[PDB]
Amino acid sequence: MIDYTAAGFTLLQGAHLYAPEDRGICDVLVANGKIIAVASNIPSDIVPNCTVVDLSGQILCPGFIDQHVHLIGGGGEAGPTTRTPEVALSRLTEAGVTSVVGLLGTDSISRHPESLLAKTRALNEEGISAWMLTGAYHVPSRTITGSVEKDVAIIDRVIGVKCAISDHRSAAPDVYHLANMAAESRVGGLLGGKPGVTVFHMGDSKKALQPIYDLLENCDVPISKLLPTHVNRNVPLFEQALEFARKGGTIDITSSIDEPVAPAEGIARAVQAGIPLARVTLSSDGNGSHIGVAGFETLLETVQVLVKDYDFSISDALRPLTSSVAGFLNLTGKGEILPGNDADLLVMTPELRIEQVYARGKLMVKDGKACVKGTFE
Amino acid sequence: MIDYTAAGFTLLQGAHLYAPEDRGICDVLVANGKIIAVASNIPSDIVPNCTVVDLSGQILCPGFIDQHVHLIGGGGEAGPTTRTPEVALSRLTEAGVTSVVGLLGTDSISRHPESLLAKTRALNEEGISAWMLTGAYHVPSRTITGSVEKDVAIIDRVIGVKCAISDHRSAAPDVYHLANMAAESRVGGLLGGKPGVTVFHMGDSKKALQPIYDLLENCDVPISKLLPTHVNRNVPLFEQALEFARKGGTIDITSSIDEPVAPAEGIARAVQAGIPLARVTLSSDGNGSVAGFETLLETVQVLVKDYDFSISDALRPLTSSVAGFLNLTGKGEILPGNDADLLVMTPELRIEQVYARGKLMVKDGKACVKGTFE
Amino acid sequence: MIDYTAAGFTLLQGAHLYAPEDRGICDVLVANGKIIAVASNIPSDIVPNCTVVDLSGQILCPGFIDQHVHLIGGGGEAGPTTRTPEVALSRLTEAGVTSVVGLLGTDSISRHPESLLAKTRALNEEGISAWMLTGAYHVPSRTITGSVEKDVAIIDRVIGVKCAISDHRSAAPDVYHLANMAAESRVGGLLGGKPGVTVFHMGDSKKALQPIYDLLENCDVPISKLLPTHVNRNVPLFEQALEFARKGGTIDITSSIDEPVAPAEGIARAVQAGIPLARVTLSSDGNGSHIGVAGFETLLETVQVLVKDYDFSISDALRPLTSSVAGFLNLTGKGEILPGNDADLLVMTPELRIEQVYARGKLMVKDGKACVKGTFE
Amino acid sequence: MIDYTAAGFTLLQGAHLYAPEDRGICDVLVANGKIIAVASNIPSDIVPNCTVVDLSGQILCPGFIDQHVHLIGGGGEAGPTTRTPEVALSRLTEAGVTSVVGLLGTDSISRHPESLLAKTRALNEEGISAWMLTGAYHVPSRTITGSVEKDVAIIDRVIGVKCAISDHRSAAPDVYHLANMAAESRVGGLLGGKPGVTVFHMGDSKKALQPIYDLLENCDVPISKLLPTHVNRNVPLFEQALEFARKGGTIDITSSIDEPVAPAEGIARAVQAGIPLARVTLSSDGNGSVAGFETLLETVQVLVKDYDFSISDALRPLTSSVAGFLNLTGKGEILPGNDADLLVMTPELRIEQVYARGKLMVKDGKACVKGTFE
């Protein structure tokens, strides 16, 4: 017989699809890591050596996109001992995360952009999709090529820049160095076909989002490029966060923080405030920070609580972790399960507990446990 | 019905397939820009929406990989007027080029790596496969990030560094600066999963390859990383290149030079010298000088016609040999898994159709896909 | 017999302990430069080759911590002839100083951070404990590694940064370069486990502490990290100094200046103003600046006047020179005579005149005169 | 009663003490992380709150000092996937390592000295003794402060500089750059009270130690500062290392290499060659490649078992020899004053308990003290 295994044909059939839009019992045919067909009842013989897997009674949805993860590690705020380790592949996949954006935090003395980049590429070769934000809390930005504009333009995996404001660990930037910073990420993004976004690490200062509004006054970076994070870290900052989203911005809630505004409660209050889910993202702030290193569970736990204790549909709870993120970061072929896109799907149960995970066509999670891991796990 | 055109299924059937190694009348199933099947006589209905194409009586081989092109332009060796223009996509796809390695030449004052990088990425978006070499004739090299090792390492499209020796347009580099440069390209390559080569532009100096030998003494960079080009520019130098190839090194012959050693005459003499074709590649140095890419296909033709090379062996220096030197995974060879970079030729080797990563570039010998502003 | 001299056992017994908290006739057993026992009536045989020294009728208290000393020298404001010499070990110890923080002043053209560091280490090897502040009057800061954040983070003996404001010898810094400066010392401190404090050299400008309040408005560095010095150099600056301490800051008075507010009068006015002694430090401004080079006597002379002409208890007068300083600079094992801490103690008379001085277990002052000195004294 | 536990008194009694020089059944009194007494039969009540521990029938020797560890990680010589993780505290303490010297290898693009410095300091806080070498295979060296001399001089944990020669992953360094580098490490060391050594990663080049000899001609850096490593990587080179050791220099053998010259086979041949063990140390190159530290204890064991070295002489290359080369005051030797870095072994040399600066690291052969995130 002729050999067609190169195509890596796979037929996910029988599941109740959520792409994330509620579909019904639909099927998904994969070929070469890409979704090439989405329609109910696809013939199992339609293509050669097709690995047909029956997901009858299962839920099929798009893989998670985590845009706030300390891939190479973080912490260090309480001494060099508090420097957390690098994130393990399996730790992500088992959490549903198929796409991830890495950034740096407080420490940019013992943590470097070239280290984040290399790692970002390790994960890519290992099967998932990884990107990174140049810079860190400190402003001006310590970068790779010498300028933020240049990094976001010429370093492929860089899609924007990070920074901290209204935090006692800030670098104390002025509206000038902050506006210039966001402008370079914008321009560079245009030149390199990247989102060119600016992600602000929100602290607890009373000024809250003030630095941002000042920036909008001092330049012409679209409000759709600024992304405040950890918005649910204190009530008045979350209140302001809602007002921000109202004027067109997209806010980012972190699941790793439970008080004084829980993740689920945050996404819920947003809807109640009339913000389209499209402008609401949920990130994990994974591997940063007993002293304890943050994990990626709270993500799925948000989707669950959203469907179980708030009335969000499965389709809606998925958005802030899928379609919303890919949309804000212009992640082509991601967050959506439509023909053409990548095969980043998760197999779950109707109780929303992950069973299988597919990244670009490969099986990362076979039974809720990773069958694929980092080279030294 | 259900929609499967997302997979862009295409079946090239009934052609005399050379991959380059002469197979028979083989069929090639393509899906998502990938060759997913190669076995004679494949069903025209094996896969759903399959664009089936009848290539009966035609030749099918891998597209050419040209590793010496001044993508953003070159020249300038006689004033700013002599600065050649950038390369047009259709120009490449029509000469049967599906993968190319850009680089800079003498002028590295009005030509910068950031621009080349940009042009390389623009080409990849448009349909073909492009990479680039950092630096230029100048040593030490004007890089993007500060060091050659860092460029090759972290700039995704840099596969090695370029430079110029035994030429009257060099920077008069000394063995140490030279050695260090290559070592950085080599180390960088390992860190970036790049071949980490060092391409040497050869001039007409009596010294010829002496600097490349001098380098071997002062460092440990494998000889499989040192690639001299334009070896066919003067006979005394060509002779040495052959001796260099006999030692395990690879040599690059430029199809844009027709004397004293013509391209074909070059690839030919190597075989006679007893050099596995594996260590011989053919580059165009297109858009240099204004050089064109016609001479690549012409060197194949003439090799099969004027000289007595076979279609398969003639193709090698322009495909598999090149692919194996830069470690361009998935190219220069037609097998399941590799990229659907294909060329449909007549029995007389006259490119009719061209495929790049699945997409059809040349329809009637004339590109049907072009750059944004052609 | 077996040899136990390696332990360097020493029993300070019979004295009236002040740790600085008023204890009674307590004893202090040292071993390996560390205090390993504090309790009344410790048996003299308790450990092997214990050098028992009878401090009967004597006062035992913690060694002085001097956080403002020009170790490599200073001055120069009236020409290169006015460049003062380096501080001598014995000059410090004989003043009670067992721990010291070095900084630079007006001159940062002929005075360098690497020189302060080396010296800071000479003193460490010679028996006492020394630290240093990166930078000088001039802002931005001339540093060791290129950034204030990096110095405070990666150069072990650097614990913060120095600067001058409201002074005719300033570098004329703006709230921006001043806030950024304090933020880097803060972050770097976190990363390297250092206080990460910013010490301001107060001048005589009418604006007084204004630059500081502006800084608090332009960033989120805690007010507990800013330290204004020479606060008693003019009445309205000292007045403001009191208000500052009230809002949470810790002020630093310099004993070397007697008018228009004396050291003792300054520490006293502070108490009278309701400031906890914990937020009041006294430094000497030693070796900076006939033209005369400043000395370290005024320190003890403050403790004395505090107990003799104001009613401060011996225990209280010691705080602003011991427990207060160690607390503000998070000097572990210092300022406190409790088990675990270092053996930096002074032997005095009930009239508060130094007799003996111990630094990390060694005897620096045997009879009010140093029995240990700098390699070239 | 009065509280004296601040001194953390501990008495290790009735063990067969090797310091490493074979003493008899000696007792060791520890106080404040310091060995304050070493004389057979010490009172279990000599000092107040004394944690007395019965080590009857057990061996007691100094903890190992491993001077070749990629603390923050290494590798990367085959893409970013091959970048090894950082070292775990328990991993070290379980292999009997109480003092370690971190360093960087080939990758000095995604691995920086500031991180190593940070990891070194984190280790010291956690219980063990750590130092680091500045630079990497690359020459000139990528430092923290701008110059090697300045790094070794003012960065408190840098004791010298590293680099790579006669290897195919070097930076192709020339005698001048090399010499200058070592001279800076040497001068720096004097200014910082550091050994100021220069550790050379040895490759598989025919040249072998020739660069180290070439260096001796062009400068005056004492030969007691030049330390080559991995000398047991190829026999021709090993032979030279021995000749180098016969001239007063020290050689480092990596326990992570088992052919052509195994570790034991290496330490053994040196003795036969008539080299005082003083000039021979054993390193692991742990977390390199992913390399582990088991081979350190295994090289001791095998030395006492397979070969005919005594327990005392076997330990030397892993303690006193190392300590005496880096001038690590107070380590590698059990005497009053020195640090309480101890290893309780069975008669068959199987680490049972481990002590680092007084604190107990390994209880039942398994660390009972770990890094913050293990």
Image (spheres, coloured by chain):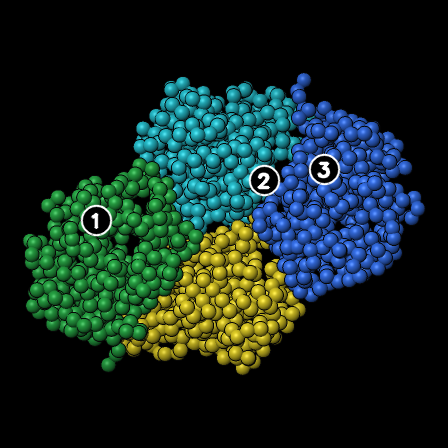
Chain colours: A yellow, B green, C blue, D cyan
Q: As displayed, is residue D37 above or below residue B259?
A: above
Q: Horizontal placement of A193 versus B99: left or right? A: right
> Which mark, residue D293?
none
| Residue farthest toward the front in the current orientation of the protein | B79
Q: As displayed, is residue D228 above or below residue C228?
A: above
| Tag 2: amino acid | Ile
> Which mark, residue D154?
2
Asked if marks 3 and 1 touch (Cβ < 8 Å), the reply is: no
| Residue C296, x across and y down, in percent | 80, 40
**For mark 3, what is the residue?**
C86
> Depth-wise, is mark 2 or mark 1 nearer the camera?
1
| Residue C366, x across and y down, in percent | 80, 28
Q: Horizontal placement of A2 versus C198: left or right? A: left
Asked if marks 2 and 1 touch (Cβ < 8 Å), the reply is: no
User: Marks 3/1: CA distance?
Assistant: 68 Å
> Which mark, residue B231?
1
Q: Secondary structure at mark 3?
A: loop
Q: As displayed, is residue D75 above or below residue C172?
A: above
Place residue D258 in its image quadrant.
top left
Q: As displayed, is residue C91 above or below residue D334?
A: below
| Tag 1: amino acid | Val
Q: Horizontal placement of C26 versus D359: left or right? A: right
Q: Chain of mark 2?
A: D
